[PDB]
Length: 129
Ligand SMILES: [Cl-]
Ligand SMILES: [Cl-]
Ligand SMILES: [Cl-]
Ligand SMILES: [Cl-]
Image (tube, rainbow, N blue to C red; front, side):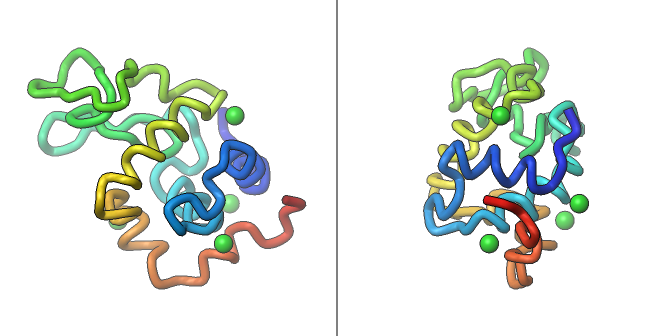
């Protein structure tokens, strides 16, 4: 599923990501834009042989099991493939754990390099939320 910007904003808000650990909704939308282009089916191999999955590009070394990442923790206790559903529930639940790990949203490279420090509210502008 490729989400519309406001569509994703509404789904993330419904799932309680808006202001979660202090990160306003535009932060999450901005992160999803640059991680996945709002595409639930996005997958990307990392240098270390791990792969990032879904709208928030959740990694197979720590968070989900993909069956091919040596040393996998699966701290979210899910198959990585569950993170590719058109229903974002598993991705959000897992993202809540990630953002609570101590580094906040800095865990998302794309957030740190493309969203942090910018007018992230722009990402929810026009949305009926
Ligand atoms: Cl867009
Ligand atoms: Cl915002
Ligand atoms: Cl959803
Ligand atoms: Cl980046």
